[PDB]
Each structure stands twice: as structure tokens, then as C-alpha cells.
Length: 315
Length: 315
Ligand SMILES: C[As](C)(=O)[O-]
Ligand SMILES: C[As](C)(=O)[O-]
Ligand SMILES: [Zn+2]
Ligand SMILES: [Zn+2]
Ligand SMILES: [Zn+2]
Ligand SMILES: [Zn+2]
Image (tube, rainbow over all chains, first blue to last red; front, side, top):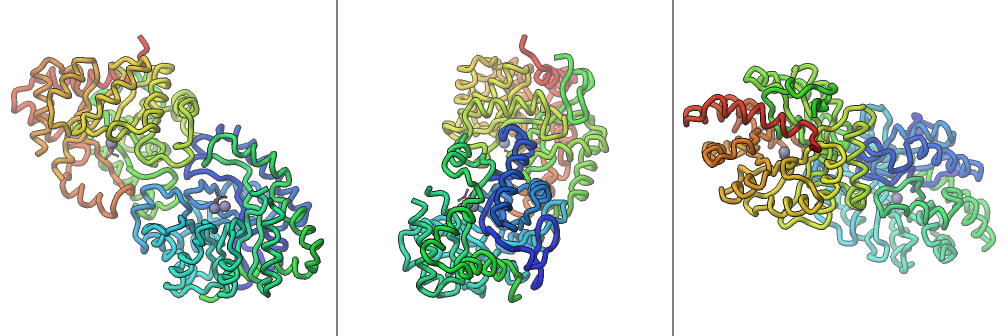
């Protein structure tokens, strides 16, 4: 809080975070799936070793902290997160919230009940681990459904109660952040607590600048998903040129295992981006400096902006 | 079949005794009990309630229950083993899939689902070494394409292990007929299959035609009408009078906690049926005796039929 954020190894001071990737995943899965069917990923051991190798390579490239925005329904296994964080010596911030696959036991809950679930994971711990979430992740479809609106209100109330930020999954093509922002502001949530994710898939700079002008963080968090990735990277330069350097968060949205998709999509992605989570420091950062963006600006985006974002702020 | 697998290890068929073939400790979602135990008061409170309820059923003669909670109903086999030990009631655990599969299950091929069911039967559930003794499948309507994949994977896992298949369907739609067609297309003998929720049938001829084909008929939700239950119970006598006593399985389809529905539904259900899982022995058995059914027939329904069904059989 304030001076410190929760990680899966415990609280760290904001200065320790360093180069932070604010939207990543160790595993994209489903609640209970890794523990019920680890051989889907070869084995749990095989999956953890893959994640440790990849995190160590991102660390070599300068990454010091990642935010795993896998929720309960993305199969978040915070014991796996802690194992790989410790072995890679990379800070991992865990998430609460709900993505696009809530089971019935979540889909039938009230906004008050969802609020208590998010407060439990932030304030008490996830499962029986004592590991606390440092961010609340919400996904909506283009047109926000009734249940998704409940999740956003619960996220806003939990963020207002704890100071931890909210990060969203959007369809940038449907300008979904505008619906999300309206709801979140209807609860009194400051835009400076909110990242509008998957924004690098947008064909509408005006949509991005208007949100940034309101104080939202712009998650250009899927750049290596292109990947033309050069065109998506230029959105970073575009927002810098308009005076919104401080509103930019950059990430890879990479994963080391995937079960919530057609089998073998992980291999396809690995042949496309062998850098994995190292893609931002190894490719995008030098691309931007080559375009004349000063080093101090890039340090602001990769260190200072996440630190201001992740630092529990306001109420 | 000699032995059947339970949550405390293998037992001999004679040890099973009076067996309720369709029950639940908890109706939930994958990962939910471990993520949000306070939804049930606490894990300890749910466990103590389940132990008291199973001890009640045991005092009324029950020696074994089949918990047909699947992965996606939030089956927690460690909870089942704890309550089974404390109540001294055998519990048989289930694999398969019910009506709430997450994305990581919905996107699997029939061959992949077959490997998952086989893992839970032949190796164990999660990391517990507890092996499933039945395969539970649910369908809706005329069966969806994915539900057909589950039925075929269930038949293949049954054919390789001898473990039986038990289904959820809508008797009002005669949904057992579509299930039977698919399972028979795979080569599975009807004597390995229980068509469940059949006591919701308004049509005796639908059940007779299935029984005459060799299916087990799951008259498994009698006290749900108590929330007329005697009318449902008469389907038991009707099938007895038609000569199909050998095809009858009876149960309560009760639960001690429920999160996959509206909040406090468990309170409504407990006030409607305070007998819980003892409803079958304390209400339905005496009712059938007063209607003239002899002891030998009732013992055949509650002991012999579940033994033959659960005994792993390929011959
Ligand atoms: C599985 As995704 C939209 O969060 O990268
Ligand atoms: C979990 As049910 C109501 O299908 O027995
Ligand atoms: Zn997303
Ligand atoms: Zn993501
Ligand atoms: Zn059912
Ligand atoms: Zn059931």
C-alpha cells in the first residue's frame, strides 16, 4: 500500500519493481484445469520450467516485474506463480477479478457478493496461500453484458476500498473502453486507477487519445501478437507525440501454456515470437529509441508509469 | 469387477451395501470451494454438515453413496475423502463433464476428452491418487455437438476400464433416447449405462422401452418434487410391476452445499426436505412397503442393482 505493492513473494517497495510488464500470463487456462489435467501441458514440471526459462530471459533483457493478469476463470494458479517467480527472481503481481469464462458459481453472484470475493483476494489472500492480489482484472465483450457490468461495479468498489488498480480486456475495434469507463466512473472510480487493455489492436487513435486525455492508462499490451508489430509500436510514439507519455503502459500479453484455445496454439505463438516476454525490451524499446524517442521517456513508460499505476492510490 | 474404487481406496462389491447411486457433497464449480470457501460459511462448516448428513443416511441403512459431481461441478475429492472417513460411509467419485464445462474443456477433441476421463479412472484425480468409479455425462435437448463428444469419450473410457456411465437428461424431452443412440453407436452395452433424472418422466412408456433395452433407469431425484414425490415414487412400483426391477436405481440427488445456483437455494431445499439423503430410506422405502413391495425386491433395488452396475464389467 502507498509505498508497497503485493507480489507473489510478498510485498515489495515500488522502487524494487523496475522495468515492469503490466499485462502477461504464466498460463492461460481455466479454474482447476492445471491441477486436474497437468499432462495437457506435458506436465506441471515441464510448464514451470518453461516459464522459469522465459522469465529469466526477460530478466536478462532488463525486466524486473511482471503483472500476471490471469483471473480465477483463466485458471490462475498462484502457487505456480510463486514457484516460477522465486526461481526466475522476477517479481510477479497476481490478479483478482473475472475474465470472459466465469463458471455458474460466479455468473449467478450479485455485485455485493463479487465485491466480497475481490476484497478477499486483495486483503486476505488467494485460496489458502496468503498470496494477495495487486490488481483487479475485468473483461467485457464489445457490448458490455449485464453480468459484465456487475463485475465492473464490483471491481470499482474493491479498487475504491483498497487502492489497487483495475485493468481491462476490451475489443479496441469496438471501442469497448468507452463503455467500461462510463460504468467505472458511475461508481466514482478515478480514471488514473484504470488501464484499458488490448488497445494496440485499435484502428482509432482518436479513441485512444480521448481516453488518455481523461487520465486512463492505455494498454498497448499485445504488441507481439501481430507479429505488423511495427505499426502497433507506432501507437506508442503517436501518444507520446500528443503529450500523453504518462498514460502509456506497454506489455507482451505472452503466455507459457495455453489450454483455453485450440490445441497447439502455444507452439504457433512461439514460432512467431521466440523472444516471448523479452519482446518489449529487446525489440520495441530500441525501435522507439531509433525513432528518436529519448531514453528518459522510455524509462518513464516502463518504470515510472507502472509504479504510479500499481501503487495503491486514493482510497 | 471384484473391486470398486472409492475415495478411501478399493472395496469389494459385498462391502458396498445399500448404495445411493446419484448424490453430491457439494454442487459447485471447478476451483470454487478452494477460492471462496466462505461462500459456504467455511470449508470446515460444509464438511461438518456433510458428515452429519451422511451419518444420518448411515443410521437409515445407507453404506455407500456415488458422488456424481464432475470436474465442472466443482468436485473436491479431498473433501469427499475427509467426509467419507468421518462419517464411515463409502463414497465413489466421478469423472466426466456436466453442463458447465469451461473453455479449456469445451475446445477439446473427443480423443483429448477420452484421455482426461481415462486419467481420472486409471491414474487418479488431480494429485490425490483417488480414482473415479463412474463417468457422469449431462446433455440438453437433442444433445449439442460438444455434448456428443463427451458421450463418445465417456463410452470409450467405459469400454477401456469397465467403469459405468451415468447420465443427466431431460425426461420430459425423452432425452435418454438420443443418449442411448450415441452410446450404442460406440459399442457400449446398455447394461453399463444409467439414464438419470428419469423420475421427472411423465411418460412411463419412455422408461419401459429403455429398461427393456437393458438400460438402468435412474429414479434419482424423488425429494426434489418435495421442495408430488409419491407420484414419482410410483414409477418405481410401475417398473417393478412390469418386470424390470433389475433395471431400477433409486437416489435423492441431494447436496450439502450449492454455489452453482442462486444464493440460499440450499436453505430452501433443506426446509423442503429436512431428511436430506435419508429421504430414500426414511420415506420412499416405507411408502413402497405399504404399497405391497416385498423386502427381497427392495433389497434387490438398493443393494444388488448398484453392485452389478458399479462392478467394473467388460464381460
Ligand atoms: C487470452 As487473452 C485476451 O487475455 O491474451
Ligand atoms: C447437479 As443436478 C440438479 O443436475 O443433479
Ligand atoms: Zn484479454
Ligand atoms: Zn491477457
Ligand atoms: Zn443432473
Ligand atoms: Zn446430480
